[PDB]
Amino acid sequence: YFQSMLAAEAANRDHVTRCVAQTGGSPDLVAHTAALRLYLRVPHFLTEWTTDPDRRAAVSRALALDIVSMKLLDDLMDDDTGLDRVELACVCLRLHLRALHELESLARDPKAVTDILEQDAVHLCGGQIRTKRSRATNLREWRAHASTYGSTFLGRYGALAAACGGEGQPADSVREFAEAFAMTITMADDLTDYDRNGERDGNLAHLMRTGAVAGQDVVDLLEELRGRALAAVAAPPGAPGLVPVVHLYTDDVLVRLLPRHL
Amino acid sequence: YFQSMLAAEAANRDHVTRCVAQTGGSPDLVAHTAALRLYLRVPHFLTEWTTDPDRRAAVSRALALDIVSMKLLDDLMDDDTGLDRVELACVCLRLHLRALHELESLARDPKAVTDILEQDAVHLCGGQIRTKRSRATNLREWRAHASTYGSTFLGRYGALAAACGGEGQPADSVREFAEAFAMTITMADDLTDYDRNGERDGNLAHLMRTGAVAGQDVVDLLEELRGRALAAVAAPPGAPGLVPVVHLYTDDVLVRLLPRHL
Image 1: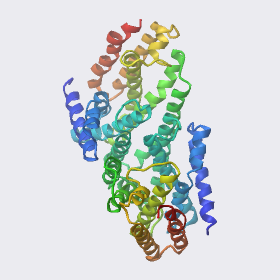
Image 2: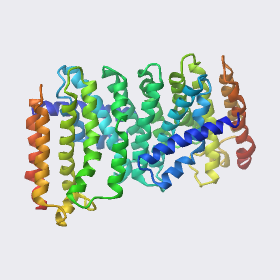
Image 3: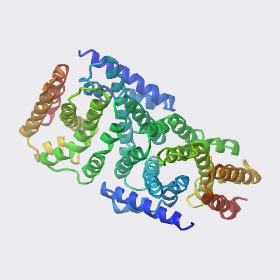
Image 4: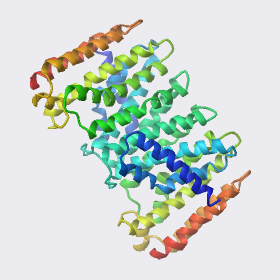
């Protein structure tokens, strides 16, 4: 297995850069995206409940298209990227439309896509604006912040995976998994991002340094998330394949990232 | 009539700012959007072939949502706006999703929306990237540039208006009208933009100043576009209401803008 997830990570990486390029992506931008490993890979975990190998691989790639799309729109707003402003926007919009197209023809009911995508957009976009306006000060906040720009974000994709992915999928469980996993990745981020490229206002690693957030509680949260996740992959039929993955990621924060800010 | 188009411009301005705000738009951003008059108004012209007053008003507002959406994504890339980076992106994405939702429930066949939206995206996004990479040098170019980032852009919306707008619409004519009108607005732009906020590389007003573009030809192009437009509103059944509008806009470039760079 810890292979096939690289196999997908690879296919999707192709399909995406294929697009990025044929729309006018420059060497730098195709490079940039080709290197967005986690993004390219997550669509795999979300489609895990899909039995047909082809549909599964079709949705998997379709979702990567949109996840990278959003990722570029993000670089457009942080603007640190140093990448070209124009390319970013156009390629972003291009990938997005293609994803919409693809996801929509994979889904049993075409309406479902825009439904899922709209049905809580207000929360995710607002959630994201607030997150950066009133930067958080203690784990109770940071958490509620990350539970929108992170959980609700990937959560939607999971919801999509279930609808496009083919009849007989435990809709809620996929979503639940997505949300837990998403937040675990979020924290994983902030801890890499405090060191790797000095960031600090409302950043979980700082709130730990500043003694505003309890090491024991970060760990508690982490594990509570591993709980939520593992639980969902367990709901019937279930995704036994994702169990190693859950532990893999969560374990990684504990083992390699948490030690630094403790 | 030259009333009702302000009546719509008004309704749409509401619906849009209503959204901008309830998603966390700041005073400045709601202000900014509230002021995007032409954008807010164009959806009116495109829905002119729709007979039912309510559907017409529903599609009209739905299209405004996405036109402003793209407009914000544009400010995000030029980044001159001086507006907040984050808000822009989130609000942008928010409006966009809402538009997708709305347009999709108005359309007879839900697939049609993403179809229209995808079916040539490659051309529009690439077209737009190129446009700014190899900035044009003579009317023959500027034109072909503006015929993507401008004509194909609004063209799609017109295509949408026809599909969402309700059975019995001259699909092609709406689109044709849109494209002509779009390019007439484009030139209208570049000429305002050379003076108003000193812009100059690949800008039609400059290519005129630099004697690289013939005054007589700009005028010829202009009028050829009024031709293409008027022709389309004339195809059966036809939009007699748009005839005054066509002339109004095109006339305006001749009368007030062209005199400066001649």
